[PDB]
Amino acid sequence: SAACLAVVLSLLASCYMFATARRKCLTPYALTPGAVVPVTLGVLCCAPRAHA
Amino acid sequence: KRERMCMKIENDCIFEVKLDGKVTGYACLVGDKVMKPAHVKGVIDNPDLAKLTYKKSSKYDLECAQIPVHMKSDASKYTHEKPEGHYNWHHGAVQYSGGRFTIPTGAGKPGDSGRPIFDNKGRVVAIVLGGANEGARTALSVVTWTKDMVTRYTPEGTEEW
Image 1 (cartoon, rainbow over the protein chains, first blue to last red):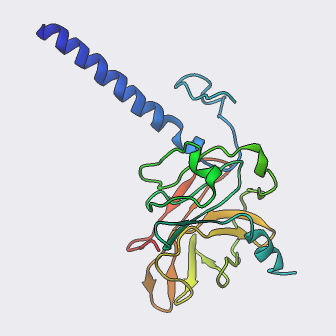
Image 2 (cartoon, helix red, strand yellow; image 1 turned 90 degrees about the horizontal axis):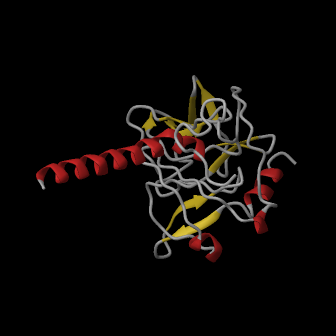
Image 3 (cartoon, one colour; image 1 turned 60 degrees about the vertical axis):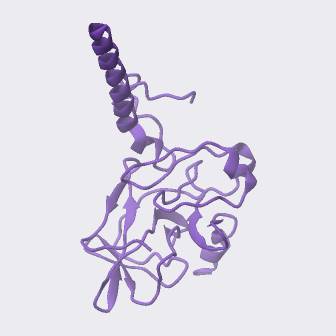
């Protein structure tokens, strides 16, 4: 049970900090007037898409 | 025709936000989106803007959210130029020098954030937050971009309105 708790907390923390990293990836490029996803810098390297 | 364009484009763009009759921040309309200072709380006056979900920023204290297609007639040009001149916001002109935005003392007051700054060609430049007093002139704090990657510029001791 302790091993299972350790692995589940590790995976949960990893997923949470992946989410934080995803936010930090392009929260500035969600901003700025006009513009689009860089594409040439990242297309799906950090899942930076929401429809169009 | 010099600042008549300014007051004409000021209408239908700035929106009112007040907790209880206390105007705190104003919302702009450019870039197919809406910006506002996230450090100050409130509620938008327009019912349509209230229901739509909105993002949030930690240290950049800005915000971006998608606008629907029934207000496509209130968008500015949003192209970046960096000369050393004037940009004449809603109260007074604007003095710029050494990469710094500067205002005459007494031309602004606390609780007046949210006023956008746009070049005299009718083209939005940045959004004003506030500043601090050093002598006969007061500094500013705005956000500037080069086609992307908005960046802040806050001199030491600055204080947002």
